[PDB]
Amino acid sequence: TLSILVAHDLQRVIGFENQLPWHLPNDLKHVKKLSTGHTLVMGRKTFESIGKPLPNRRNVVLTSDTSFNVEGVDVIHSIEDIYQLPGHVFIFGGQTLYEEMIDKVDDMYITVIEGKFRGDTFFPPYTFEDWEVASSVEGKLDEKNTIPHTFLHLIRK
Ligand SMILES: NC(=O)c1ccc[n+]([C@@H]2O[C@H](COP(=O)([O-])OP(=O)(O)OC[C@H]3O[C@@H](n4cnc5c(N)ncnc54)[C@H](OP(=O)(O)O)[C@@H]3O)[C@@H](O)[C@H]2O)c1
Ligand SMILES: COc1cc(Cc2cnc(N)nc2N)c2c(c1OC)O[C@@H](C1CC1)C=C2
């Protein structure tokens, strides 16, 4: 199983200066829950953003750099290597990966952040004409989680 994992705002911003533009613990708990015991694929920039392997799952980092050999982390140098990986594979970011994989994944788990932020990286445009809403569940707003947000599970029609 090949899935995208992404959080994006109303204009499909995903990134600003190699960080997330928003602070939203719920989303991060969601990511954790979904991908425990499974595999994350991710481009070098996103990994260096996170700065160390994510515990309790297989971290795979896609890079052109053949000197890459980080403890905790498996490296690949081709998009095609993704299809070799066993198990549930989540495409974890960032923009380059999403663009490369979006026509290939079986489904997407998306957090829509119901705000407009300044970004420098984006999720590719997509149509619900192409993608069916298997579930839509509103994040809960609270002291700690203060932007409206919706958990979409979409599956390719
Ligand atoms: N909202 C979210 O859910 C979310 C999730 C993840 C990331 N982000 C954001 O996304 C932004 C980063 O996106 P980005 O596109 O700039 O970076 P990125 O996708 O994380 O990484 C790009 C790098 O990945 C490697 N790569 C990609 N495709 C490759 C290929 N086909 N073959 C070999 N290597 C390949 C290359 O590394 P090398 O140059 O080393 O070869 C490339 O420079 C950040 O702002 C981050 O905060 C948001
Ligand atoms: C740009 O830096 C980060 C990028 C991601 C990828 C990501 C985040 N949220 C969602 N809904 N999907 C993702 N693929 C995550 C992240 C980042 O920095 C912290 O935190 C992780 C932490 C919660 C485990 C979760 C995903």
Image (spheres, rainbow, N blue to C red):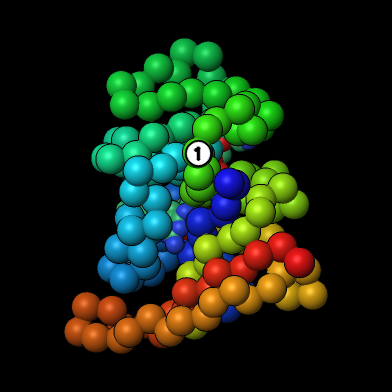
At horizontal 58% and vertical 46% (from top left) the residue drawn is 1
Q: Position of residue 130 (x, y in %)?
A: 78, 68
Q: From what the image shows, is residue 38 above or below residue 63?
A: below
Q: From what the image shows, is residue 27 above or below residue 61?
A: below
The number of numbered badges drawn on the structure is 1
Specify the quadrant of the image occupied by residue 107: bottom right
Q: Where is residue 100 in the image (x, y as percent from the top left)?
A: 70, 44
Question: Is residue 116 visible to us here?
Answer: no
Q: From what the image shows, is residue 28 above or below residue 71?
A: below
Q: Which residue lies furthest to the right in this view?
A: 129
Q: Mark 1 points at which residue?
A: 87
Is 104 situated left or right of 39 in this image?
right
Q: Is mark 1 on a helix, strand or loop?
A: loop
Closest to the observer, 152 or 65: 152
Q: Residue furthest left?
A: 143
Mark 1 neighbour density, 10 Å: few (under 14) some (14–19) many (20 or more):
few
Ligand 2 is found in the corner quadrant, namely bottom left
Q: Where is residue 63 in the image (x, y as percent from the top left)?
A: 55, 27
At horizontal 28% and vertical 79% (from top left) the residue drawn is 145
Q: Position of residue 30 (x, y in %)?
A: 36, 64
At horizontal 53% and vertical 14% (from top left) the residue drawn is 66
Is 65 situated left or right of 28 in this image?
right
Specify the quadrant of the image occupied by residue 73: top left
At label 1, the amino acid type is Gly
At horizontal 44% and vertical 50% (from top left) the residue drawn is 18
